[PDB]
Amino acid sequence: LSSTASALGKLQDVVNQNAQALNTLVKQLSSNFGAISSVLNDILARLDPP
Amino acid sequence: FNGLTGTGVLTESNKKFLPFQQFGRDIDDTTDAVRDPQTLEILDITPCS
Ligand SMILES: *[C@@H]1O[C@H](CO)[C@@H](O[C@@H]2O[C@H](CO)[C@@H](O)[C@H](O)[C@H]2NC(C)=O)[C@H](O)[C@H]1NC(C)=O
Image 1 (spheres, rainbow over the protein chains, first blue to last red):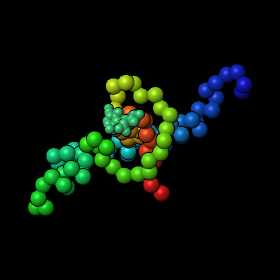
Image 2: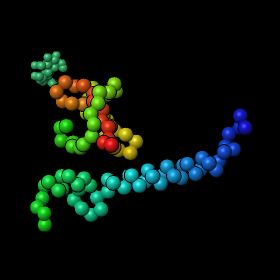
Image 3: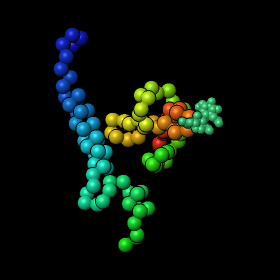
Image 4: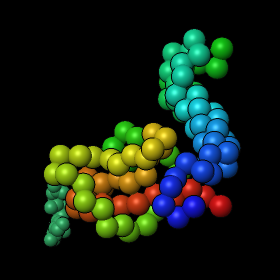
């Protein structure tokens, strides 16, 4: 156990999968989605309500 | 702070901004530190509770 690595493959795989899912969830906040800007404050404060 | 807007808790920090860099960043592209344009002192940002 002490010298050789990659024995604990399964637990590390679980952790990596969870981290990747959470990261790609967070990263989806900068997409335009067809609007004119990703950030909501400027678009709310720059145009009319309609 | 100079165009970029947000909310949170301001704190004093000890980062090492390069002489031309304005605001720091994180792994997920979330603003972390800023440099106030009046005394050039690095400044840290924390989310609310
Ligand atoms: C902008 O103006 C401010 C204030 O007029 C200047 O602030 C000085 O900051 C230094 C250290 O950061 C202090 O030793 C001085 O006493 C401050 N001046 C005053 C009048 O309080 C600042 O240097 C100016 N320039 C910039 C680039 O911010």
